[PDB]
Length: 106
Length: 106
Length: 107
Length: 105
Ligand code: HEM
Ligand code: HEM
Ligand code: HEM
Ligand code: HEM
Ligand SMILES: [Cl-]
Ligand SMILES: [Cl-]
Ligand code: NA
View 1 (cartoon, chains in turn brown, red, orange, cyan):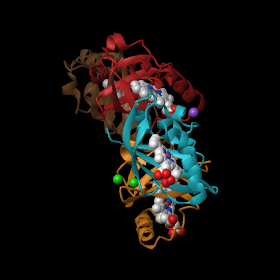
View 2 (cartoon, rainbow over the protein chains, first blue to last red):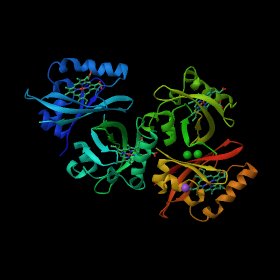
View 3 (tube, chains in turn orange, blue, brown, purple):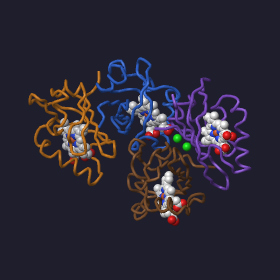
View 4 (cartoon, each protein chain N blue to C red):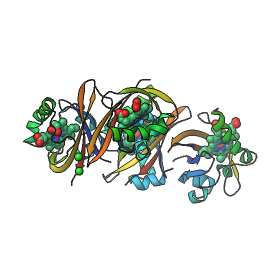
């Protein structure tokens, strides 16, 4: 049943990668944790994603947080697929984390 | 940064339940989803938790969101344990969800 | 009456207890506040001097705020400040002094 | 984390810490507004009001600043040994008493 869930820290590093995220993206949770979230997308988003997070931390002007967007994901096997993305922010131990929920559109 | 994560909707219904949550509380994600998150807690919190959610949706005045709190959790086998909670708020598909990080303090 | 935001420190300003209402007011959970100096809860230069306030009190026994209370400026985890009324008590446990603080948010 | 209770100076519970709830079995909301004498067996239970009143008149302490091992009572009625430390503080010209409870079990 459930959609894929990914948590990142304030610098884009994967901290949690749900069971449905493993099935969808192909990475095991252990492989995904400690990698930049930018591994889960094609170019050009892959190269720009660090700047997207940094721009948000500086300005607190959201573009997908609380808004959602249809984007293209990339699996461990290199294939791409359309997906809808919802993102949230929270604080834990005084530091920011971002929660993403991924609906596989295919 | 704890590995146990739970996501609820705006009525306290479990939407996602991470593998570490499963081990800690003793409920599988498949069983957990669709149940109120209050199954994971002892009284008196159990019977009041819906009112805490509704109160927050009314006031927007967090008691735990962005602050954190040590509370008592209850496992499926009825045993209780100290845990720290970090809760965040997010929106997906136009509705609120709450993201909870659970740190077992046993 | 008395406030529900209560803080207990030892004789060196280290937080020992941090009540639920104090967590909400200051934005720190007890897990992180306990073991830190109470001076984390105040702006400068009070923060840098608060240890001296306590230690000089323990040597002189001349109270300023104890038993009287005072409106002071507090500071939250997120760095925002706010006026607050502070009531302080002193007690002994196991031959060591502790101080009990009750905080009223005046925002 | 240790059990703390604050009374007014008729013995009514004002604050009841999380460790206090775990120890005595009363929720904070239940405890607040009850006389602290609920937390002890007889004969102390029936006499505790007089002890506070006697302190307020005489200012002669017996446990304040001194401490004592006494017997406490849980909500479920069971008794247990505990060490108590008590302090006084004022606000509004009215005393409040702060109690720290060590469960000796
Ligand atoms: C895997 C496919 C993903 C793609 C293609 C993607 C793409 C993008 C894009 C295009 C933006 C900038 C939006 C704009 O400027 O219009 C952005 C921002 C951001 N993304 Fe992602 N992202 C993906 C996954 C994630 C995940 C899983 C998370 C968190 C777990 C995340 C966190 C963020 C954050 C925190 C921002 C800054 C906040 C904002 O601008 O609203 N991203 N992303
Ligand atoms: C399982 C053990 C849990 C316990 C004992 C518990 C207890 C509480 C308490 C006591 C409050 C109110 C604070 C107060 O009135 O002083 C509260 C509020 C709330 N809880 Fe929980 N909770 C638990 C788990 C969760 C989880 C896992 C989530 C979300 C995934 C959650 C979501 C919320 C929300 C949204 C509020 C209101 C927001 C706020 O006041 O900051 N709870 N909870
Ligand atoms: C967080 C905001 C606080 C501020 C801005 C603050 C400020 C001060 C100041 C300015 C003094 C010296 C008073 C003077 O000499 O005129 C003082 C003394 C003192 N404070 Fe604090 N304080 C704070 C919190 C606390 C808390 C929560 C406690 C105890 C739980 C505490 C315990 C003491 C003690 C024991 C003294 C010396 C006793 C006395 O002067 O009567 N303080 N504080
Ligand atoms: C729950 C178990 C408790 C027991 C068995 C107990 C027992 C006693 C006894 C025997 C005395 C008289 C001392 C004497 O005459 O030698 C006394 C006095 C007193 N108690 Fe308690 N007490 C308990 C809890 C508390 C708590 C939790 C507080 C405050 C938060 C408190 C506040 C006082 C005060 C203010 C006095 C008078 C002050 C003094 O004589 O030092 N008591 N108590
Ligand atoms: Cl003592
Ligand atoms: Cl002792
Ligand atoms: Na009550």
